[PDB]
Image (cartoon, rainbow, N blue to C red):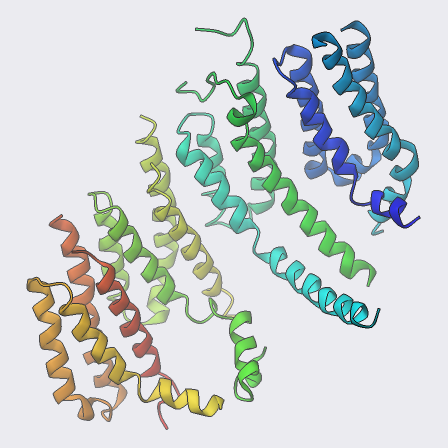
Length: 465
């Protein structure tokens, strides 16, 4: 019964895959397109109403066997169109009566070195589940954006709207998923009913193509992502249904490692949303990218984390209304993905901003003492690799900060901070300018990182020592 249980968990999808095979067996006429609709219906209900999906599993697979029958009976060329439906119904039969019930039971949440390997593999599995439970709205949202940024239309536009107004306001995430699934399927169905013989000669999305699979492959993978996400949610639910702190940082190296895998975007988050805005204005360099520049230099200027936390409400609204408007002006567009990667990062820092409200010794010396000195070498090599006028400015700031450096590393925070905040302005200006007047931004971005890291060392409690 080992293999029966394997089939009572990892083989229902064979029936689903076969559904597609039938639907895409050569020239798809109406009946093959309805076959697709049936496959879609199954997977869609899985998301919408899990309980009801489970209620009509094998019954519906047998109703499908009923479809395949009629086809083969009525309709070598003709025999190949009988063969495939037959193959489909055969697979169903096996699950239908023999593995369907123990599957409804697997979904019911309501030598020497082999044992060692099994334990190792077990650890991995559990951990990976946890990660993919929380980091999956990301990949869903990113893929539905990459698809609708390539195929600009007015029927894939709604998908951008969904995953770009549900990332800032994260209470909509469930309904985003729901409406995306139905709509992606509407797209799939319409585009297929356009590969017909009576449908012959684009803004609205629907067009004609000749690998019918290749054409409707993109939007099919989206349906896939969406559904796979729900599987992971419920699988992890089942696992626990049935069956890295601050202190750890100051103990061993592994203790610190854990603290950061747990929280990295918790702490270093304002810094990463600023290093994502520098990427937009470095890969796009147009004119609509200059407003991202002005936001950076009006958020950075309020130097207090608390004040910045009152402007984040508007930074996040702007970045979402700008992606939509720039894609309305691209329909009447594959670099607008940098305006997404940043609506993601910034929607996530809006979350930290409302949730904070609720041999290792060797490394700490070489980060909190001999790093100011490495930042100063980078300032030199930021301005002597790119020969320009702006580059001379960097050379001359290195010279000042090397001479009056010892005094700076000693002064009270007020002043240390003022001086480091001035050097940060030069960089943001060489970045906003190199754009307005157009050798690039890469070396000024390595620098913007280092200087934002040292602002954190100079404001710590470990620097007091």
